Image (cartoon, rainbow, N blue to C red):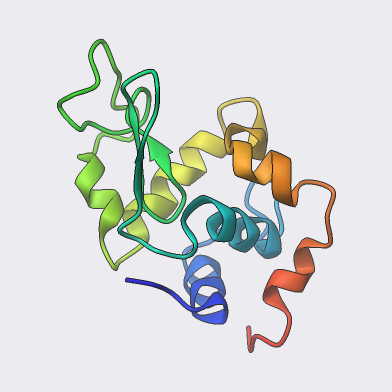
Amino acid sequence: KVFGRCELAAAMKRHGLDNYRGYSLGNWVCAAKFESNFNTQATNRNTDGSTDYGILQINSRWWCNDGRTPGSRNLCNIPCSALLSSDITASVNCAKKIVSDGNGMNAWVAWRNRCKGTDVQAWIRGCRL
């Protein structure tokens, strides 16, 4: 599913990301924009042989099982394919663990490089939230 911007803002807010670990909703929407272009089906292989999955490009070395990432963990206890669903619940639950791990949203390198320090409330402009 390709979310609209305000559609995704509303879903992320419903699931508790606004101000989660102190990160306002626009940070999360900005991260999804540059990680996946709002596409839940996005996947991208990494040089280390892991893959990133879904709206927040959650990676198979630590967080989910894809069966092809040797000596990986599954700290979110899900199959990576769960992260591709139109229902973002599993991606949100796993993102909450990731952002709690010690480096905050710096775990998403698109957030660090394209969202951090910018006017992230622009991403929720106009939305009825």
